[PDB]
Length: 130
Ligand SMILES: [Zn+2]
Ligand SMILES: [Zn+2]
Ligand SMILES: [Zn+2]
Image (tube, rainbow, N blue to C red; front, top):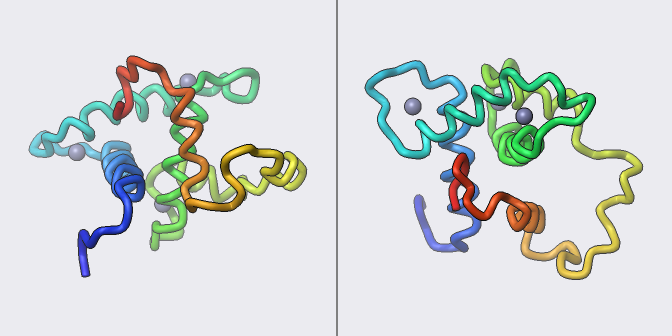
């Protein structure tokens, strides 16, 4: 069983994550993918983003979302991607942020509820997949 039906959201998430983990380390001139080359932009920006602690940009936050999926799929405990291990060091639990409750649509259903954050992505999304 490979590429079996389920839901396109899972696939969209997969393509984005796969392209991100790869682009973050892709040093090969051979590699030529639209997702790989666009991801280079966000990874280069985020690798230089230190203002996060004061007031980071939106890309700084949005990157961490997809990297958190790879964080649970990285077999290597010493993740080469710097944001992957950063998520591990934070847990992402919040432990007091409101337990992710009070939503209208998202009562622990769909399994990809976080996807609603893409609704705030730029309408032009010149750095991510529209
Ligand atoms: Zn590549
Ligand atoms: Zn930034
Ligand atoms: Zn990893």
